Image (spheres, helix red, strand yellow):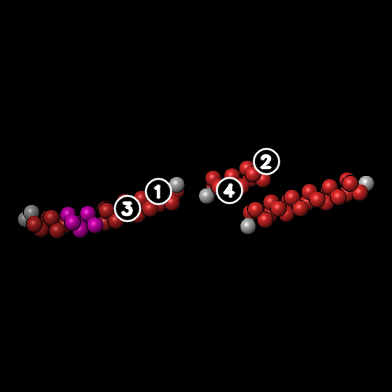
Amino acid sequence: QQIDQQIEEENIRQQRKALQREIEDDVSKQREIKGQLLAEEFERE
Amino acid sequence: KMLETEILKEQQMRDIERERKLR
């Protein structure tokens, strides 16, 4: 039974990555939004 | 005596098995 659950302990060490993927979305959006907004700043002059 | 032997040795397989599960 301990081995059965020793394996589960590793199964659980194996959500952070999906948040990491999200981290990159956060980065891309803000980076590109700054460019979109500067393009808007000119359009809005 | 041989049974306690074989058991105490056998258990170390179980600890190698732990090493094997870690791989």
Which is more N-terminal, label 1 or label 4?
4
- Within 10 Å of disc 3 (Cα), the crowding (few <14, some 14-19, many 20+) is few
Number of the front mark, 2 or 3: 2
Identify which amino acid the numbered label 2 is placed on. Gln
Residue at figure coordinates x 91%, y 49% from the top left: B2
> Left or right: where does residue A38 sit relative to residue A23?
left
Circle number at residue A19: 1
Identify which amino acid the numbered label 4 is placed on. Glu
Which is more N-terminal, label 1 or label 3?
1
Q: Are marks 2 and 1 on the same chain?
A: yes
Q: Quadrant of the N terminus of chain A?
A: top right
Residue bounds of the magenta highlight = A32-37
Circle number at residue A10: 4
Question: Circle 3 is placed at which residue position?
Answer: A25
Question: Circle 2 is placed at which residue position?
Answer: A1
Q: Quadrant of the C terminus of chain A?
A: bottom left
Label 4 and label 1: CA atoms lie apart by: 20 Å
Question: What chain letter is assigned to the residue under label 2?
Answer: A
Identify which amino acid the numbered label 3 is placed on. Asp
Label 2 and label 3: CA atoms lie apart by: 41 Å
